Image (cartoon, helix red, strand yellow):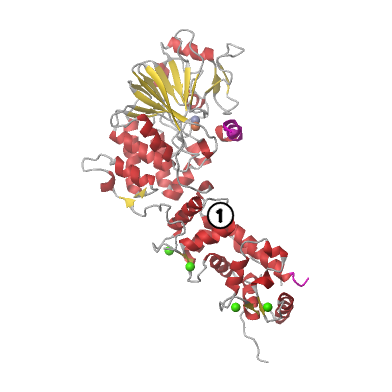
Amino acid sequence: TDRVVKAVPFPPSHRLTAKEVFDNDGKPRVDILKAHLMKEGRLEESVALRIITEGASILRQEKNLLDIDAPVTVCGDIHGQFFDLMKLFEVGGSPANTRYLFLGDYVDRGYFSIECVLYLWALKILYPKTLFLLRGNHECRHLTEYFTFKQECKIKYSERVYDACMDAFDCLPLAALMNQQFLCVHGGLSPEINTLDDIRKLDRFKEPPAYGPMCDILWSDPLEDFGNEKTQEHFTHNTVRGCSYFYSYPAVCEFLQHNNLLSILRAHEAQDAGYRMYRKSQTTGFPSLITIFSAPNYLDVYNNKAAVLKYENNVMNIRQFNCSPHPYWLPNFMDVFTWSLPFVGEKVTEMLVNVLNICSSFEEAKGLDRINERMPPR
Amino acid sequence: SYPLEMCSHFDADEIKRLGKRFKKLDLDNSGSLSVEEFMSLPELQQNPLVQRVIDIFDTDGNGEVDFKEFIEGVSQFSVKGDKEQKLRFAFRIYDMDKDGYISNGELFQVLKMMVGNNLKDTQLQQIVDKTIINADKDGDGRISFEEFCAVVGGLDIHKKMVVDV
Ligand SMILES: [Ca+2]
Ligand SMILES: [Ca+2]
Ligand SMILES: [Ca+2]
Ligand SMILES: [Ca+2]
Ligand SMILES: [Fe+3]
Ligand SMILES: [Zn+2]
């Protein structure tokens, strides 16, 4: 063929059928799924939707606040970095023999968001009682309409798939109590959430409201000077997210003691090391807060390591990992025609106008990324 | 002696003007403009698509642009031209072998003429694969003018492919 860079793998034209995706017992065939997605193949739309809807039915029956036992591997933000997700399972262990908890933010930013969801939802159908998924702030219509996930679905699939995902995202639990010691949430605390029972009383099946306990769990961040605050104040509006709050070491210590908990494990903020252990609780000597970020070389520019948390034998071990190669895409999935046609029209016209007139760093990436980390408008 | 036949949107006057420019460009007064006669203009030496335009203009494939060819190529840019004609011309910028279809290799090479080394070839190859994948609504693995148009028609780039004579 005409193909110049012959060695580059070309995406399969075959769309997997239901029989190729679900065995005769209705169990997702994950190895076949993983392989096709890694080559950038797609599924028949109906098969994709089945994965989404079957996944949502299982999530829908789960509690706002899940109870998860150790050993477990806890994971932070993925952000459609499908190829780093494959690496993450290698470092974390097979979900066949491993309990998993994901803290949210499966989509946006990365260009393999629908693969992450189809793959994760296939794993939830297969391991409904050992692999768990929480809602992150990006798992909503508001952020996915603003960032690229809605467009991605439109390119690779359809708005129908996008919608099925929005409905499925409304079903995701909001927190998890792990080994009866850790409260695991995507963002963090709320002035309006004092005990674990308060999370149980929320109605989560909805687009996250603009204000409130649900918005807060998903969006809250620890103060920038968490642990060394100049005040014993608890919550102050989150000027970084432009919504919800910044919570302090004293707010956390209070929540922990009141709920007889050891630490809050959350994700949401990119970390150069893939994680961050905060100030040790005065009472236990164990970090009062731990951030887990599981998207290496976030955005292809942060150059950060990623990490997962593996709790077992009473050892909370952080397993860091580096990025993996993934295919290339133009911004907003722009095709090369639309990309180059302007330059063509401009340059050939310019050519002829001329002829006729013959006769007359992590932080760098971070600060640069600021607006993208805040609550999109209205 | 012997009239010259041609197809163009131009009137007698414009054809006479274009003939004058054609003469000034025709260095060796051979009656056919050459690549080097074209490249004599410094404004053109800093333009990646000069050889694509000359080739599209050079309809008889002899390597030079005769007067008939010059007038018919410049006519694609007449203000009197239709959307289709201008898109057809854009289509032919990628369609190197003039088969009426943009192939993967043709697409890689023409884009490569414009992107250069802002993209590694692996990257450039992947976005060409996916662009064809999405636009190739016939499964022939190549882009017809119809498929090409389905993608770009709404862009209205033809409105900018207009020169004054
Ligand atoms: Ca000449
Ligand atoms: Ca010729
Ligand atoms: Ca061709
Ligand atoms: Ca085709
Ligand atoms: Fe995030
Ligand atoms: Zn987040």
Residue A278 painted magenta: no
Q: Is residue A299 left or right of residue A311?
A: right
The answer to whether any part of residue A201 appears in the image is no
- Where A283 falls versus B164 (above or below)? above
Q: Residues within 10 Å of mark 1 (few under 14, many from 20)?
A: some
Which SS class for mark 1? helix
Picture mark count: 1
Q: Quadrant of the N terminus of chain A?
A: bottom left
Query: Residue placed farthest to the bottom in the image?
Result: B1
**Which three-letter amino acid code belongs to the residue tagged 1?**
Trp
Ligand 1 image position (quadrant): bottom right
Q: Position of residue A17 (x, y in %)?
A: 29, 50
What residue is at 28 percent from the left and 32 percent from the top? A96
- Magenta span covers which residues? A357-370
Instruction: Write down the residue under mark 1.
Output: A339
- Where B144 falls versus A97 (above or below)? below
Foreground residue, A155 or B16? B16
Q: Chain of mark 1?
A: A
The answer to whether any part of residue A297 appears in the image is yes
Foreground residue, A23 or B129? B129
Query: Residue placed farthest to the left in the image?
Result: A24
Q: Position of residue B20 (x, y in %)?
A: 74, 78
Q: Position of residue A88 (x, y in %)?
A: 40, 33
What residue is at 57 percent from the left and 57 percent from the top? A340
Foreground residue, A123 or B150? A123
What residue is at 45 percent from the left and 13 percent from the top? A286
Occupied quadrant, residue A164: top left
